[PDB]
Every structure is written in C-alpha cells, then in structure tokens.
Image (cartoon, rainbow, N blue to C red):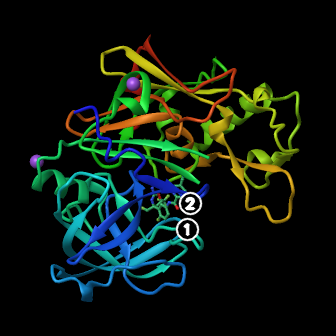
C-alpha cells in the first residue's frame, strides 16, 4: 500500500496523442503500447497491418488465444472500429507482477481511429461493463484483473503534460505523486466514471447557473479526451466569463471556438491575463463539497507541429459538448486522480508533476458548504 516504485513513470505520450502504457498479449508475449482510456470499457488492439501502426496483435502467434466467434462494430462521433472478440493472457510489464485472461477485440478495420504518427496501437478501456460493446456481458479488463488476482480494486493516474509521461498505479496509490490531501467525490453511477459538479467559478466568480446545467446529461472523468468539454449552455457562460477576465488582450472569436490557434513570440506567453477555472465537486458528506482549480497552462494547449509558423502557438482546449461535461486531460493533468472503484469514489489531489508558474498553482481545497447538491444530477 502507498509505494509502487515499479509503476512510477510507466506512461508515455506526445502532445495531442494521449497517454499509453506498455502491455503484453498472448503466449509468447507480444508487446504493444496501449492508450489509457477511463472514458470507455473495451480492450481493443489493432490486429492487422494498418499503415499508421508500429506493431499489431498477431493472434496466429499466440498459443493461448481463444476465439469467441463474435464480431463487434463500434462507431463513435468521429471514428469507428470493427473487430473480432476473443480472450488471451495479458500482463502489464511496469504494473503488478500478474497475468490474466482478458477479453480482447482484435481490430480488423478502422476509420479515423488510429493517429498517424502516434506510438500506440490499441486502447485500454478502464470504465465499467455497462458501456462495454457489444453489451455488458463482455467483462472489461480491470474487472478481469481484480476477479482473477489479489490486486486491490482501484487504480490511480498521474498525467504529466508538456513528450508527455506520467504514472498509472494499478492496485494502489503512490503518495510521492501528489502534495496535500486527496479529496473524494462519489461515483454517481458505475458506467462511465460519472461525477456531479455543483458549482463553477472563473477566477473566483461563480457562473451562477442552475447546477443541473453543469451535469446535463452527465459529467465524466475521461483520460481518452484531451479537452475540458462543457454542455453548450455552460460553455457559452464560461467563455463569456473567460473573455471578460482576459479582456486586456483581444483574440479573434474563432480562437474561443477552437477554430484557430493563437501565437506569441517564444518565452512571452501572457499566462497572467488568463483566469483560473474551478469546478466544485460533490463531496463525501451531506452538504459538503471541495473544489479543484486549474490554470491556463492546462487549458491553453501547445501546438508545436504548426509547420506554417515560427512562434509558440496554442489551442483553446475548453469546448462545447452535447454529451455532458468531459473532464479530459485538461483537468487531469492538474491532479493525481484516484479511481477508487472499491469505495465508488474518485479522489483528486494536486499533482506533484503539474505544469504551473511562480504566481499560481493547481489546487484542491475543502471543505465548502454547498446545499441541494443532489438536485445537480440530471436524470
Ligand atoms: N491528452 C490526451 C489525449 C489525446 C488523444 C486521445 C485519443 O486519441 N483518444 C481516443 C482515440 C480514439 C478513440 F476512439 C477514443 C475513445 C475510445 F472509446 C472514444 C472517444 C469519443 F467517445 F470521444 F469518441 O472518447 C474516449 N474516451 N475514447 C479515444 N486521448 C487523449
Ligand atoms: Na481479487
Ligand atoms: Na504526498
């Protein structure tokens, strides 16, 4: 408990392309890099020579592969993949010293799913069976891991933004990865890691919306999405408020919509004109909340691959959503996040690796008194 040196720094990535862990599949073991995704629940790996893939699962080479004789077709808003379901032996080399028999979707066809240039070739869905495809009888990886071993039913993620890196501690927490205290919010329902946001402030100024708007139709914590995505009506109020707070510089409207980049002369980003963003989350106790605060260093994302420019260019990474709030890597890179599935709750603490400056830091503070927090959930 509390110290897992073998798992520290077991994540890698590049800006824009997410965080992956090494895994092995099959006998003898085939090494693959796998995107860590708390926003889905399938373990799905490229299993054919798509041109974007460094490596892919070759079932023919595994003596322990078992075919389930069942296909799956999985479309998302953008992107889709199709695969053939089976089971095989899976390990995490920089993870617990265990091997488990897990479901795997061998991806045989995909569109807009793999990233050209990335170094990962499958996804590890860490959420619950309820959103597994094709249905909840396909047990997710982490459920198999916990049923089949003595690994405790929890994992924690420290995502260190811009090469990016970080740690996924499987079966515990490592107290060297955060400072101050962990504060916990209840998992409202086990499907996504759904939570309830009870208040939102921009530089300490409350947006004063009906709090159900913050969770319409849900709010989730999702390592497989880059942005902080907010329900449209909340996005509108938040942007209006951020524009006001930064109004000593004027930016094109398209910037706030994520339709164009903004660039400054190198080493001169005016961090201090941009406000901090605070989300208050439902706490463990009746009428008690806590708040997490992030900086422009989290929500203004560096874009380095801008071949048509010399300067430091950034994308605004808070965007409008029609699927609820998504606390993607913009939120998670401020914090050490504990997915305490055994107690159905999510812990946040200030990350020991988060990007900040001499004036401001990411923060996790409580307790606050917040009434009617159960009305903030959408049914
Ligand atoms: N930081 C960062 C960062 C950068 C890139 C990325 C990245 O490419 N993710 C990725 C790629 C294809 C994918 F199909 C998905 C999916 C898989 F289920 C669907 C996606 C949705 F539902 F939104 F389509 O939401 C989530 N949660 N997972 C995620 N992830 C994180
Ligand atoms: Na167990
Ligand atoms: Na600590």
> Which residue occupies 58% across, 47% down?
227
Q: Which mark is residue 17?
A: 2
Q: Label 1: which residue? A: 118
Q: Quadrant of residue 349?
A: top left
> Which residue occupies 51% across, 53% down?
225
Q: Quadrant of residue 98?
A: bottom left
Residue 326 visible to the viewer: no
Quadrant where the N terminus is found in the figure: top left
Residue 233 visible to the viewer: yes
Q: Secondary structure at mark 1?
A: loop
Disc 1 residue: CB within 8 Å of ligand 1? yes
Tell which of 297 and 278 is nearer to you: 297
Q: Earlier in the sequence, mark 2 or mark 1?
A: 2
Total residue callouts: 2
Is residue 344 rendered to the left or right of residue 49? Answer: left
Crowding at dot 2, Cα within 10 Å, few <14 / some 14-19 / many 20+, comes out as many
Disc 2 residue: CB within 8 Å of ligand 1? yes
Q: Secondary structure at mark 2?
A: loop
Q: Which mark is residue 183?
A: none
């Amino acid at each position: 408990r509390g110290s897992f040196v073998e798992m520290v720094d077991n994540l890698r990535g590049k800006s824009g392309q997410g965080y992956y862990v090494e895994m092995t599949v099959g006998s003898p073991p085939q090494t693959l890099n796998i995107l860590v995704d708390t926003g889905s629940s399938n373990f799905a790996v490229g299993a054919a020579p798509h041109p974007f893939l460094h490596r892919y699962y070759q079932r023919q080479l595994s003596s322990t592969y078992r075919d389930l004789r069942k296909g799956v077709y999985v479309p998302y808003t953008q992107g889709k993949w199709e695969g053939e379901l089976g089971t095989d032996l899976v390990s995490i080399p920089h993870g617990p010293n265990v091997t488990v028999r897990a479901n795997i979707a061998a991806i045989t066809e995909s569109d807009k799913f793999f990233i050209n240039g990335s170094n990962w070739e499958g996804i590890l869905g860490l959420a619950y069976a309820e959103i597994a495809r094709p249905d909840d009888s396909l047990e997710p990886f982490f459920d198999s891991l916990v049923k089949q071993t003595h690994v405790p039913n929890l994992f924690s993620l420290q995502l260190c933004g811009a090469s990016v890196g970080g740690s996924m501690i499987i079966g515990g927490i490592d107290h060297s990865l955060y400072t101050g205290s962990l504060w916990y919010t209840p998992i409202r329902r086990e499907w996504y890691y759904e939570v309830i946001i009870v208040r939102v402030e921009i530089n300490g100024q409350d947006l004063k919306m009906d709090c159900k708007e913050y969770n319409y139709d849900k709010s989730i914590v999702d390592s497989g999405t880059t942005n902080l995505r907010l329900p449209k009506k909340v996005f509108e109020a938040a942007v209006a408020s951020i524009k006001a707070a930064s109004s000593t510089e004027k930016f094109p409207d398209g910037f706030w919509l994520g339709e164009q980049l903004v660039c400054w002369q190198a080493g001169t980003t005016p961090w201090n004109i941009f406000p901090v963003i605070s989300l208050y989350l439902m706490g463990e106790v009746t009428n008690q909340s806590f708040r997490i605060t992030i900086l422009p260093q989290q929500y203004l994302r560096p874009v380095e691959d801008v071949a048509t420019s010399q300067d430091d260019c950034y994308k605004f990474a808070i965007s409008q959503s029609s699927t609820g709030t998504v606390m993607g890597a913009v939120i998670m890179e401020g914090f050490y996040v504990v997915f305490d599935r055994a107690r159905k709750r999510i812990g946040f603490a200030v990350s020991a690796c988060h990007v900040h400056d001499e004036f401001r830091t990411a923060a996790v503070e409580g307790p606050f008194v917040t009434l009617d927090m159960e009305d903030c959930g959408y049914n």
